[PDB]
Image (cartoon, coloured by chain):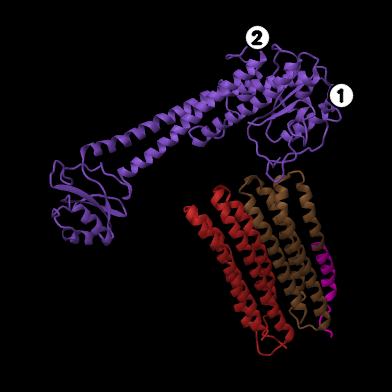
Chain colours: A brown, B red, C purple
Amino acid sequence: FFGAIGCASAIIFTSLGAAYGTAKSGVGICATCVLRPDLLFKNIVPVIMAGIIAIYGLVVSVLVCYSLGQKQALYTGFIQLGAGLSVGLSGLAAGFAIGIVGDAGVRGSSQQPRLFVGMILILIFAEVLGLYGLIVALLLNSRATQDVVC
Amino acid sequence: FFGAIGCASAIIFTSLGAAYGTAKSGVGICATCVLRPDLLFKNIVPVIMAGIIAIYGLVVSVLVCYSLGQKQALYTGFIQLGAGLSVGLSGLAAGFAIGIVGDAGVRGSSQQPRLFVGMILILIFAEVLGLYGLIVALLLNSRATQDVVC
Amino acid sequence: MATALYTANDFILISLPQNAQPVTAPGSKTDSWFNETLIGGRAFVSDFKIPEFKIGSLDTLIVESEELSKVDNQIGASIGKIIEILQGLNETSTNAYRTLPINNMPVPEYLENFQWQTRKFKLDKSIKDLITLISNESSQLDADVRATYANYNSAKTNLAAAERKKTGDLSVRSLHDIVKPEDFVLNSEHLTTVLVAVPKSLKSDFEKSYETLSKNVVPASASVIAEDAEYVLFNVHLFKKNVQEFTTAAREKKFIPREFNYSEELIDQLKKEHDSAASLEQSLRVQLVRLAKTAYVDVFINWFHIKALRVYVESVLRYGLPPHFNIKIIAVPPKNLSKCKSELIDAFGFLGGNAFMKDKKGKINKQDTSLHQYASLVDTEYEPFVMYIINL
């Protein structure tokens, strides 16, 4: 019912999130590298911020799979739903944050090698959310499975 | 039924993802080909990266078909619907990201031939999102295959 | 760092009073400090001390500083233009002329043997004529490089033109590579030759039509004297009256006539023109590389003398006593420039005075802003002790 759609949401939302991040940042970086090819390594570290959202997402998703297969009812379905959404929204939203900050921060990385740590720190504030989605979800998964029950 | 939609999500979305990626990549590559014509082989490496997503999607879909009975259960049904979604929307998202990064990175190819691999390192980061889809969808399929026992 | 690339030895020139003490390391001498303390002990410190010359007056001291600042720029402009040329041609390393040997001795070592060098410059000449002399030599050497480079571009233009005649494309191509008496007529009262540049498709059409196209045309005169890749070149023999009628009738068909008419003196003069262009460019190129290295070593010696003189003079003006000033030139390892600039500022800046002291530390090499870059010239900020940053 909603529980399957939970699985699904987790994967839909966080993938897209991470895409958005990678695209936005990517274009800025690709452009920048032509000035100085020495910012290769620096530049990559903003892009890898959106790569980690999804891997957390896979851990919550995989759990739900094991708890699924059987015909359930309302009780399992809604608690599985809510867990999906959690990894889903953080992935989407944090993913969104990172690409914005990332692009403008490619100018920061380029001119400032010593306020580069400052640049990480802005990005690092978005990573807080990824955690929140995930921790709440993990808790949710274990509790959700009761199987059936309207 | 809900099986038909499983099939639908996975093959529509991921197909468009691949199309997006190639189109976009194309526009850059064709601008760039007049400028430097022997960097063709390198140019070519991004284009094919988005193409391999589709072939995963369509395999998931052939299975999902088989897993549809005619007994009709909402909850077995929903896992197939939910399964299709996961590779669909992840596939779309990798494709959208890959064409943007792909485009911007051919400018890189032109100016800095030597450091072409830095574009690749970026691009390949949105393949994780397909793996994440693939894995989760497969399990979900496998659970589902029962020909919707009511 | 990563806001600037360095891969060649960088220099900061300091001059300080010989009674000075660093407050970043109290209990040290300035000389002992440079070697041991400064950038992790990895600073190479070189001698750069020069003695007293003859100073006009205190009054004269002022006039000298102003000129020194100006001549230093101007020589700097010249040496940059010579290096840019040698680099541009890529017949000599592009990866040197920042730490390329002067007098076949490595550049940090060259400065270490630099104590006031003699080429034409002595310590018993007056300071005003050394400022003047030096600048005149630098300007002459650069003006020479500029003229020979100017000549080398006029030579490139001539070699392309001449080549095009020798085999190019028919819209200016003049013939002298074919010299046959069977494809052209000469010593002739009634006949002349008109060359017709014909598209390759249209070659068949030309072959059929030409005899009847104008009246009074030598038949079996069609021969392919030359061919390019877009056009075919034919020779036609015809009446002098009838040449006008052929050029005009041919254009209607979409043939392009090339007005050429056989004379020996034109053919010989086209071959000579091509020959002299080649010879001129080749002589100019060798002369251009030889001249640029020789001029470069002399201007390097000239430039560092103005920097040595200047730093000493500026010290004499700002500090007065001691009459001999402790000058050292420090060769900094790549990417440790930022750290170097800061440690000296902290340590010595106090001697110049608290008013003199401003914080705008940091460095932007990109054109996003023009703050954060020291120079006493600007009112925006000032150096807080006699310090020049030298970037080759």
Q: CA distance from mark 1 to mark 2?
A: 39 Å
Q: Residue at x 69, y 31 (%)?
A: C333
Residue A149 forms part of the magenta stretch: yes
Residue bearing mark 2: C124
For the question of whether residue C46 can be seen, the reply is no
Quarter of the image with the N terminus of chain A is bottom right
Q: In the figure, is residue C325 to the left or right of C212?
A: right
Q: Evaluate if marks 1 and 2 touch, with contact meaning CB atoms under 8 Å apart.
A: no
Residue A32 screen position, x and y as percent: 64, 50
Q: Is residue C305 above or below residue A14?
A: above
Q: Amino acid at mark 2?
A: Asp
Q: Is residue A26 above or below residue B71?
A: above
Q: Amino acid at mark 1?
A: Pro
For the question of whether residue C213 can be seen, the reply is yes
Residue bearing mark 1: C26
Quarter of the image with the C terminus of chain A is bottom right
In terms of secondary structure, what is the magenta stretch mainly?
helix
In the image, the segment drawn in magenta is A130-150
Residue C77 forms part of the magenta stretch: no
Question: Regarding mark 2 in the picture, which secondary structure is present there?
Answer: loop
Q: Is residue B20 above or below residue C376?
A: below
Q: Residue at x 62, y 23 (%)?
A: C303
Subunit of mark 1?
Answer: C
Residue density around tag 2, few if under 14, some if 14–19, many if 20 or more, within 10 Å: few
Residue density around tag 1, few if under 14, some if 14–19, many if 20 or more, within 10 Å: few
